[PDB]
Length: 152
Ligand code: HEM
Ligand SMILES: O=N[O-]
Ligand SMILES: O=N[O-]
Ligand SMILES: O=N[O-]
Ligand SMILES: O=N[O-]
Image (cartoon, rainbow, N blue to C red):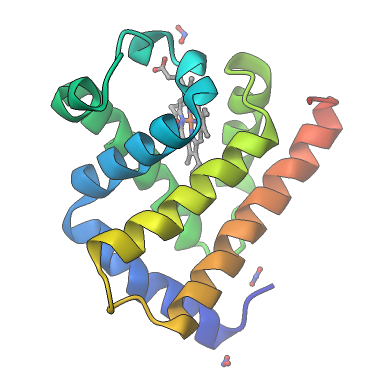
């Protein structure tokens, strides 16, 4: 797990996201979709987005970005005690949305990139370490639920 000190760093970094949740959420999804176009295909409601300009101009994409990072934020503030919060998301993403765990790796990497891009020089080595650990814990606990469900 993470140390108390590491959790404190995670939640300090998260303060950056909370100041502009829509903007961070939008950039995370754009980074995901542009780096990994196969991920766009999992969203019927974003499939029409044929260019990054269209992605940037999509108010619904920003809306979903807010939904996604709000959910993640709630999970992070549980500091690993997130079974109840994580369970339903693991279940919907495996069973309904059919999201391979690899795509959760992609979006985790996208979050790290967006933090550096929006806050260059203000996302320190210790902070990256802590946030990376938190995202790995999140992914690992989702993966356990995926295995329960036999989802690949
Ligand atoms: C930080 C990781 C993620 C979080 C916190 C997250 C969160 C959410 C939430 C809260 C919802 C709405 C409720 C639900 O259906 O469970 C949702 C819907 C959805 N998610 Fe995710 N998600 C994540 C990663 C991903 C990834 C990587 C993909 C695909 C590559 C994905 C695909 C979808 C799809 C297709 C929906 C349904 C969208 C709609 O039609 O309205 N999710 N997600
Ligand atoms: O504190 N990590 O679960
Ligand atoms: O929990 N202090 O590393
Ligand atoms: O954007 N992930 O639902
Ligand atoms: O209507 N089920 O998303």
